[PDB]
Amino acid sequence: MDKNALRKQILQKRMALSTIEKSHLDQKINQKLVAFLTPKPCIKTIALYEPIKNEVTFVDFFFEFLKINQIRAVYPKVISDTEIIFIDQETNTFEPNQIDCFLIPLVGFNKDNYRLGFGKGYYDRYLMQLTRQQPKIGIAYSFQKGDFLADPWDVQLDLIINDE
Ligand SMILES: Nc1nc(=O)c2c([nH]1)N=C[C@H](CNc1ccc(C(=O)N[C@@H](CCC(=O)O)C(=O)O)cc1)N2CO
Ligand SMILES: Nc1ncnc2c1ncn2[C@@H]1O[C@H](COP(=O)(O)OP(=O)(O)O)[C@@H](O)[C@H]1O
Ligand SMILES: [Mg+2]
């Protein structure tokens, strides 16, 4: 349904979310997230993101679950307008394969688990460098589901953790 039309629609529905609901959906999601990792304590370095246009938020206790398990959290930083890189708190940059798992922010997703981002293409571009079959998990509210045809360059997400 044209990636652009489906963006404005979902993005707007997400911006109209009430604090209490958002809170109720982020809590649920962060919990499915903690229960998602524990059963495979192999992730030593994980890719997160800094919630922006009302995206799913990462809660305090989630950051604590990573703290007591010595898991490093690296975040995306746009270099120019070409590519993005991932760095940690001390600002050291970790190469693509130094990252064991990617928790990705998104606007929408279709039945084939393809992502719909801001339209820049940084993630599709980046996530092609992963040669370790690292998990590409999309984080999102259950209503971010959308019907759109994927382009040849679109990266397919392995799992889409949502409030369900
Ligand atoms: N929290 C988060 N959300 C994201 O979806 C996002 C992020 N992290 N992680 C890195 C990339 C970068 N996404 C970007 C999206 C848009 C523009 C951009 O074009 N900015 C406009 C601003 C609009 C304006 O004021 O005109 C510009 O042209 O300046 C840059 C980077 N990304 C994707 O998952
Ligand atoms: N892996 C890639 N290599 C080269 N160009 C890309 C790649 N991925 C995306 N692009 C370009 O960047 C743009 C990103 O648009 P789009 O895929 O719709 O963004 P989004 O993933 O945020 O929905 C596309 O028009 C495309 O031409
Ligand atoms: Mg794409």
Image: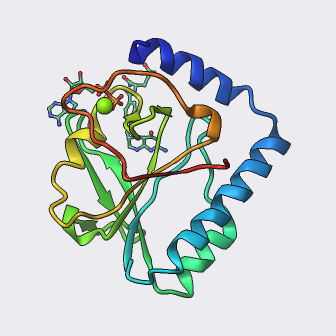
Between 122 and 6, the one lying in front of the other is 6
- The residue most toward the front is 111
Looking at the picture, does residue 77 appear above or below residue 90? Answer: above
Q: Residue at x 41, y 41 (%)?
A: 113
Q: Residue at x 63, y 21 (%)?
A: 12
- The residue most toward the right is 20
Q: Is residue 30 left or right of residue 4?
A: right
User: Measured from the top left, where is residue 73 in percent x and y?
Assistant: 44, 69
- In this view of the protein, can residue 65 be seen by the observer? yes
Q: Residue at x 54, y 80 (%)?
A: 38
Q: Whereabouts is ligand 2, in terms of quadrant?
A: top left
- In this view of the protein, can residue 95 be seen by the observer? no
Between 143 and 121, the one lying in front of the other is 143
User: Measured from the top left, where is residue 39 in percent x and y?
Assistant: 51, 80
Looking at the picture, does residue 4 appear above or below residue 15? Answer: above
Number of marks in picture: 0
Q: Is residue 116 left or right of residue 161?
A: left
User: Measured from the top left, where is residue 35 in percent x and y?
Assistant: 60, 72
